[PDB]
Image: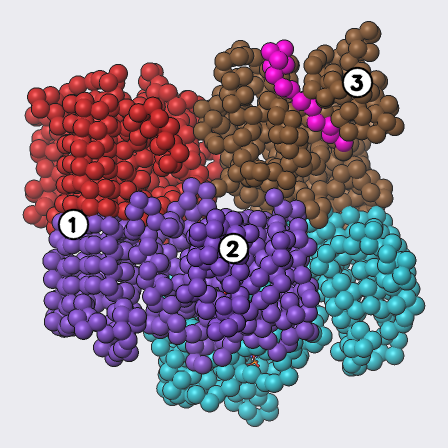
Chain colours: A purple, B red, C brown, D cyan
Amino acid sequence: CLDPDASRSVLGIILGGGAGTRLYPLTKKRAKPAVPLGANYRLIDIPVSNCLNSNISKIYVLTQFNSASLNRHLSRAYASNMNEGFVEVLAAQQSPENFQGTADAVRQYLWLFEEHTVLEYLILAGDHLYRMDYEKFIQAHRETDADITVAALPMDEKRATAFGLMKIDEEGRIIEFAEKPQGEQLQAMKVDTTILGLDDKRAKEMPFIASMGIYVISKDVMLNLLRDKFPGANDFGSEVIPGATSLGMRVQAYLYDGYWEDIGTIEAFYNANLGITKKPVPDFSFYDRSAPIYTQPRYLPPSKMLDADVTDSVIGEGCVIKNCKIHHSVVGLRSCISEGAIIEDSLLMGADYYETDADRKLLAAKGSVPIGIGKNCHIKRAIIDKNARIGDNVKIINKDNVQEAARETDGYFIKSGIVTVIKDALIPSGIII
Amino acid sequence: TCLDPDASRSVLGIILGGGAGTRLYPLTKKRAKPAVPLGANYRLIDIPVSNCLNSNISKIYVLTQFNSASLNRHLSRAYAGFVEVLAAQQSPENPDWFQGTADAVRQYLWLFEEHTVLEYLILAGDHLYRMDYEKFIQAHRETDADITVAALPMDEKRATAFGLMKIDEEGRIIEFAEKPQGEQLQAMKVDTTILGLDDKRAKEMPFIASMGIYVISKDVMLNLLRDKFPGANDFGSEVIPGATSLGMRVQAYLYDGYWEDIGTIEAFYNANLGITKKPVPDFSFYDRSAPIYTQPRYLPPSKMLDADVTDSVIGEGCVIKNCKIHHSVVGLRSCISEGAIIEDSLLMGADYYETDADRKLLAAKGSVPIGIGKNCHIKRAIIDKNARIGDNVKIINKDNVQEAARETDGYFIKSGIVTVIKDALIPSGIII
Amino acid sequence: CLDPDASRSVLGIILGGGAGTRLYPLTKKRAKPAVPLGANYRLIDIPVSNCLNSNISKIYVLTQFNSASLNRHLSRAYEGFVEVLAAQQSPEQGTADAVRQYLWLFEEHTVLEYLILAGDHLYRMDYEKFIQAHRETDADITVAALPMDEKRATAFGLMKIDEEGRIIEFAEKPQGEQLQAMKVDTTILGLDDKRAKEMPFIASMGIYVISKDVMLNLLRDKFPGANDFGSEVIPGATSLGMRVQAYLYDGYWEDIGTIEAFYNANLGITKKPVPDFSFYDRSAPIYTQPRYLPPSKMLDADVTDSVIGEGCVIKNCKIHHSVVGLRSCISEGAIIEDSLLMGADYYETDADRKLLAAKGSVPIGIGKNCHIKRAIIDKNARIGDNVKIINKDNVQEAARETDGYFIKSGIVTVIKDALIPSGIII
Amino acid sequence: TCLDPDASRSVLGIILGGGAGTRLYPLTKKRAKPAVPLGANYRLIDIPVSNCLNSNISKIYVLTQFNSASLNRHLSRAYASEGFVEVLAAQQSPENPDWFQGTADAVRQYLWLFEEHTVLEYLILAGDHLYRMDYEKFIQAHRETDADITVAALPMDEKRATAFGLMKIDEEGRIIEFAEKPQGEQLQAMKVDTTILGLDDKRAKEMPFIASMGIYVISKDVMLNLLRDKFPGANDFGSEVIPGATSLGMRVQAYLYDGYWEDIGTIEAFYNANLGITKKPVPDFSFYDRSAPIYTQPRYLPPSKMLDADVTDSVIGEGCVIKNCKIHHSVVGLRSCISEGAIIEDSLLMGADYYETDADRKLLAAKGSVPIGIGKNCHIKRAIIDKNARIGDNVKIINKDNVQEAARETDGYFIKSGIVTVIKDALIPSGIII
Ligand SMILES: Nc1ncnc2c1ncn2[C@@H]1O[C@H](COP(=O)(O)OP(=O)(O)O[C@H]2O[C@H](CO)[C@@H](O)[C@H](O)[C@H]2O)[C@@H](O)[C@H]1O
Ligand SMILES: Nc1ncnc2c1ncn2[C@@H]1O[C@H](COP(=O)(O)OP(=O)(O)O)[C@@H](O)[C@H]1O
Ligand SMILES: Nc1ncnc2c1ncn2[C@@H]1O[C@H](COP(=O)(O)OP(=O)(O)O)[C@@H](O)[C@H]1O
C-alpha cells in the first residue's frame, strides 16, 4: 500500500512518439502510440492500462505529433471515464513535417508537470509488452528514500548490449551504471544474479541486471536534474541516469519478475505478437481478471467464419472469414479473408472500417481491389497493416529469403526477413513477394 | 426531419421487459427476461435500449415483473439520461402470480408522471429489430394523435397470429381484432397503400398488425389507466382498443424492415442462428450509425488451437481446442474441449473464466469444469451460461422427442430443441 | 492502508427513506435522502460523499420509494456506481428488513465487507481506518462507537467492551446498577484518560462493517425474523459468540432527525470563528450536483451572520443569521432573520411572472416587505407581498397543512410549493 | 428543420483563443488569453466552448500562441470527461511570446490536423467576445445558400461602426466588399439597408452599418484552398483571407446576428463588460440560461459566508468569505476573502485559486507577509485584482492623480484607461497608496 495514495500523489508520463525508424513502416502513416497490437489493441493501451490498474489516473502521453486518430482512441477509451483524472496527449511538434530525445521531451513540458501537486513522476516507455503493478514500484521508491528508482531485471548476454546495465548493493541501490556498453565494458558488468533470486543454473545464464527504461523520479529531483544539473541532456538512460549517480544521488533499482518484452523493433514486435498463440499458456495475456489491458469499446459483431481451418491462432473481433486456412497467426479486428487464402505465421492488423457490398462494386468496376486478403492468396511470415488491399493470387513467401528491402512504392518493406505490407496499400493480384 | 422539443428532453421510453417469463422458460429460470443472453455477445434488453439511444431517447425505464442481479449489473455497467429497472417484485425468483402489462405500467404511473415529457414511448422487450423512433414520434406530433401504433404489414397466413387493425383512408385506426380467423380475419382487410406500401406488396400483404410499439401522449396515458380503464390488465389488447372505442385519436404508422418476435424458444433459437445465414443475415447487430450496444468487457481475442469452423459466429474471449463447429453460435467466454462436435447449436458461453487454481480443485475431486467436454456432441440445442458438460456427453435427441421438461436433470425440450439450464451439470457419458 | 483496496473490496449500503415522519413536512412531497441541506446540498450527500472520499466507489442507497428527482441528483452528481434501491413500488421498515430484501443483489458482489450507513447525521468520517480495525481484529462485525458521559449515556443503547474492545453486552437506555454496569474504560478504544473519564460510556452509532459471509448468514439463517440491525442482529451475533468489535469515533456528530435539530444544524454553519462542521474540506469535500448557476446578485443587501447559496437574486433587504438556499429570489423590503430558505428548483421568467400577477397568483420567492423569522421555507414557496411570519404568540405546534405550513418546536415550516397569500400573518 | 448530417459529426469548431495577449496585459502575464478569469466563476474559453456544446458541436480545437497550465487543467476538468476540446499552441511554453503570429498563420499551421477530420465545415470563432449564440441556424444558412463562407454580421450605428471591419452586401444578402475600420468617405460608402438581413425597419435606419464579428463557417475544401493555394502568405484571417475570398468571386454570404455582443479583448472593454452583469433592471448578458448556459468547472466550493456585508449592485462568486465590509457595483470572484472595514467600489476581484489555512496565516503573520485577499481597511476603487493577490491592510487603490496609463510591473500593477490592475500573485504591502 501507499500513502498518500498513487491517485493523487503520482503523475504518469508516457514516452510514446519516439519519432524514429525502428518500427518503420508501421509508424509511416501514424503516431507510434497508435500502432495496432494483439488483434484488438494499440501500443499506448499497455502503459495507460497498467497505470489505471495501478490506481494512477493522471496521465500524459508525450508524442511527436498530434493525431486525430490517437486522440479519438484515447478519448473514446479513457477520457470518457477519467474525481479528477485524465489521459492527455502532449505533442512535441506542431506538425509531422520535421532530433528530440526523451529528456528533451520531458523538459519541454516541465512547466506543466510541475504544476501538479504530486510527490513523484512515473516515466514509462510507450513500446513495451508487460503487466506491472506500479504501486509496488513506487512503494520501493518511497521506502528506500530514493531520488530515482529504475526498474530492472535479469538479462542474457546476447541482448545485454541493447540495454543500460547496472550493479547494485545489497539494498538494491545502484552503484554502477552503463548505457548499452560493449567490449571490455560489457563483460565487466557481468554480475552475480543470485542476489536477484536466480537459482544458480540460470544465474550464470543471465549475469546481467538491465534497466527496463522506466522510472519513478521524485518531483523536485526531476526539475533539478533537467533544468539545473543537466540542462543539456537529451536522453535519460544515456545521460540523466548516469549523471544522477555520478552526482551521488540516491539511485535505487527495483527488481521486476514478470514477463517483459521491448517491442520497439519489427522483429521483436512480430515475435511478441505471435507469442500470444503459444501453448499451453502464452508468456503474456492481455486479459487478466484483476489487471486487464483495456482498449476502445467498438461494439463490433461476433466474427463470422464461413469455412475456416484455424490452428494455433487468435481471432480479433468482428472478422469476416470465408473458406480459408489460418495457421499460427493473429487475425486483427474487422479482418476480411477471402476464399482459398492461406495465412501462416502472420500478423494481420485488420481494418478501420467495413466496406459495403456497394463499395466493393465500385472498386471492381475500376479494377481496384477491396480491403482484405484476396482469393487464393498466400501470406507467410508477414505483417499486413491496416486497410491493406491484397489482390487475388498474391503470395508473400519471400522465396529468396530477402532480409531487407525498402519498397514503399510497391506497398511493402522487408525487415529482418519479415514482409510488412504498408497501411492502406494496394498489392495487385498475381504479385509475388 | 427534426423533433422540437427533441426526444432527449420530451420523450420517456418505457420498456415492457417481461412478466414471469413463462414463454422463454427455462432461459428465464431465475433470470428476468431482459437479461436473457442473445447473439453471443448481447442480452435481449440491449435491443430496445439501443434503439432508444440511437433515437436520441435517453430517459429509459425497464419494467419487469421480477428483478435480476445480472440485469442490474448489465444496465449499470453498459449504460446509465438514465436506464432504470422498475420491478414489480424485488426477488430473482420467477413469480407464480400474474401481472399484465397494463397493471405493470399502472403501478408506476405515479413515477412516470414526475418526468416533464410530452410522450411515453412504449416498447415490448421480446423482438429483434432496428428502428429510428424519431420519425415515428414526429408523425405522432404532426397528426396530433393521442396514440400512434407501429403497424406491420403481412399476408393472410401470418396475420392469424397478431392483433390486426383496420384503418380509414387517413391512416386513423378504427378497429382491432385479436388473432382473427375465418370471417373475422377477412373483415380486417386493408389497402396497405394508405401507409406507404407499394402495389404488389400491398395486395400481397393486405393486413396491418400492431407490434407492441406505441407513442402515447402523457395525459392520455394517465387518463386511460386511472380513469377510463382502471381494471384493464393488458395494455395492447385492452387499453389501446379501448381508447379507439372511446373515439380517441389512434393513428397507424407503417413499419418497414426486418422484425422477429423472439419470445418463444423456437423463434428465439431460429433468430439466433439466423445470424449465420448465407449469403447475408436478415438482421445485423452491428451497424455503422445505429449499432446494438452492450457491455464493454475487454475480453481477449478468441483462441483456436485446431478448430474446423463451418458457417458459424464466434463470440469474444473464447477458448476453442481441436474440434468441429458447424452452423452454430458461440457465446462469449466459451470453452470447447478436444474432440467436441457442435452443430446447429447456440452456446451461451460463460460469465467468467475458471482459474487454473479452480481447475485444480476440480481435478482434485474429478469434478466437471465449465465448458463443453471432450468428444461431446451437441446438436439442435441451446446451452445456457456456465454449463458444466462432461466428457463423452451426447445431446442429439434420437427419438426426436418434441416437448419435454426435466429441470431435475438439468434440461428442457421444446420443439425438438434441447436447452441445458444455466449452471447445469451434465455428467460424463450422459446421452440425451 | 487497505489491501485489497476498499473500492474493490467494499460495498457501501446507505439506509435512508424509512418512514420519514419526524421531519414532516419536509418529507411530505419528497424522498427523505433528498431533503435539502445547507443551501446547496441534500441529506444523501453526506454519506455518499464520505464513502467516495473513503475510496468506497460501489454504493447502494436504500429508500422507501423511487424518485426521479433524487435519481437525477445522484445521477448528475456521481467499476463504481451509486444506485438507489426502492423498498416499495409506490409512495403510498426495519433496518435489517431493508437490507434483507436486497440480499440477492448485495450477495452477488465480490467484496470482503459491507459498510452499513444508517440514520441521518451530519459528520465527516474516513471509513478506511474503520474498515482496517475490522480487518486487523478479524472481527465478524465492527460497530462504530461514540463516547459519552453518564447524562447522555443513559439515553442511548450503550455497549460494554472488554480489555480487547470486543463488545460483550448491550443495553437500551439502562439505569441504576445496570447503567453503572455498562460503564467501560474508553482508553481501551483509544481515548486519553482525560476524555475517557469524562465519557466512561460508549454508544452504537448505526455504522457497521460486516463481513460478507457473516451478514448473509446472519440475516438469512441466524435471524430471519429480526427487524432492526442494532436492536437484534448485532446483539444476537454477540450472544452466539461472534467477534463483535467496537471502533471509537471521535469527531463532530450531529443528529438532524427532528425539525428542531435539523434547523439548528443548518443555522450552525453560521457559527462564529469556525463552525463545528464545514461542508467543504481540501481533502474530503461534500459533493453535490453541478448546476452551473450564476453568481448571486444583491441589489442592496445588509447581510450579517449568514451564508448565501448559488444563483440567488436579492434586491434591497436585510438577511440576518440565515441560510439562503440556491436560486432563492428575495424581493424589495424583505427582512429575513434566523431562517432557512431552501431556495427553488428553477427560475421563473418575467413572462410567467407578469402572468401570475395578472392571474391573482404569486411568483416564487419572498415577496416585498415580508418579514421571516425562526422559519424554514421549503422549495418553491410562493410568498406574497407583506406576509409576516413572526409567530408572535410563540405557538409551539400547529398542523396548518391546508394553509401551506406547519409549526414545530416553535419553528414555522412553509411546505414545498405552498402558496402564502399576500397580507397573511403567522 | 435541423442540420443533416448533425453538427456533431460534420462540423469542427476552431477557436482562435488569442496570440501573445498584449492588449489584455497584465491579465495575460504568463496566462494564455483563453484562461483569463471572467464573471466571478468562469474563464474566457468558457464562452465559445459552451456556445459550441450548446449547438451540438462537440469536436473542438482551441488555438493559442502560447500555452498555460491553468488552461489545460480547466478544460480537462470542465470538459475532458461526444468529442473533445484540445489546445493547439504555437509555442509549448507558458511565457508570453515576443514574436508575432497572425490568425491565418495560426490555422494554416494546423491545417494538416484539421484536414484529418471528416467534417463538412469549420466553425471559426474568436475567443475573446462575450455573447450567447446557437450556431446551428447559422450553419444551416451556410448550407442552404451553398455559400463558401458565411459571416455573422453585426448591425451598428455610425458612431460604433468606425472601430470594426464593415461589410457591404447586395439586395440578396451576399457580401461584396469590406472596409477595415473605415472613416469619413470610406465609412459613408459602406451604409446598407439592414432590412435585407431581416432587421426591423425602425432599427435598420438607426444602424445602417454591418460589421464582421469574428464568427465564420467555412466549407472544408474552401478553407484549404484559401490558406494553401490562394493566399499562402496571408497573416490575418478575417481581414486578409475573407476579403480575399470575396475578391475571388467566392460565395461569401452574410448572416444577421441579433442580441448582446461585446468585444472584451482590451482592458477597458473587458472591465466594463464584467461590471455589466450588475445592472439593476436586467443584465444585457446572462451567463446562465435555461437552455444554453455557460458551463465551467464544477468546484464543490461551499456557500459564501458574509459576516457584516453591505452589498450594493454586485454579484458574488462561490466559496467567498466576507467580513465587515462594503461592496458596491463590483464583481467578487470565487474564493474571495475580504477583511474588516474593506470598501470595494466599481471593482472586479478575480478571487483566488485556493484557500489558505489558519496555519498558513500564522506563518505569514509571523514572517511579516500578507495573506491572500483584501486586507483590513482597504479601499479598492475602479480596479481589477487578479488571482491570489495579497493586499495588505490600509492599502488604498484609488488613483488620486487620475493617471490614465502607467506600467509598473515591479510594483505589481498596471493602469489602463484609469483602471488599476493588480497582477496575479502580486504582493501589495500595507499602507501603500495607488
Ligand atoms: N523525443 C521523444 N519524445 C517522446 N518519446 C520518445 C522520444 N524519443 C524516444 N521516445 C520513446 O521513449 C522510449 C525511450 O527510449 P530511448 O529512445 O531513450 O532508447 P532505448 O529505446 O535504447 O531505451 C531505454 O530502454 C532500455 C530498456 O528497453 C534501457 O535498458 C535503457 O537504459 C534506456 O535508455 C522509447 O521506447 C521511445 O518509443
Ligand atoms: N408484467 C409484465 N411487466 C412487464 N412486461 C411484461 C409483463 N408481462 C408481459 N410483459 C412483456 O410485454 C409484452 C406483451 O405485450 P402485451 O401488450 O401485454 O400483449 P397482449 O397483446 O397480449 O396484450 C412482451 O414483450 C412481454 O415480455
Ligand atoms: N496567434 C494567434 N492564435 C490564435 N488566435 C489568435 C492569434 N492572434 C490573435 N488571435 C485571436 O483571434 C481573433 C482575431 O484577431 P485579430 O488580430 O483581430 O485578427 P482578425 O480579426 O483579422 O482575424 C481574436 O479573438 C484574437 O484574440
Q: Which residue is drawn at 51% across and 40% down?
A: C80
Q: How many callouts does the rendering have?
A: 3
From the viewer's side, name the closer residue of B205 and A219. A219
Q: Tag 1, which chain?
A: A
The residue tagged 1 is A309
How far across and down, in percent of the image, does residue B394 sit?
Answer: 16, 27
Residue shown at 71%/59% (left/top)? D353
Kindly identify which residue carries mark 3.
Answer: C184
Q: Viewer-nearest of labels 1 and 2?
A: 2
The magenta segment = C237-250
The answer to whether B357 appears left or right of C171 in the picture is: left
Task: Relative to B75, say whether D303 is above or below.
Answer: below
Task: Indicate which label's residue lies in the foreground, 3 or 2.
Answer: 2
Task: Using the image, determine if residue A374 lies above or below residue C414.
Answer: below
Q: Front-most of A235 and B13? A: A235
Q: Quadrant of residue D254?
A: bottom left
Secondary element type, mark 3 = loop
Quadrant where the image shows the N terminus of chain A: top right
Residue A351 location in percent, x, y? 28, 61
Q: Where's residue D316, x and y in %? A: 73, 55
Give me the disc on residue A193: 2
Which residue is pictured at 23% across the width and 46% down the height? B305
Callout 2 secondary element: loop
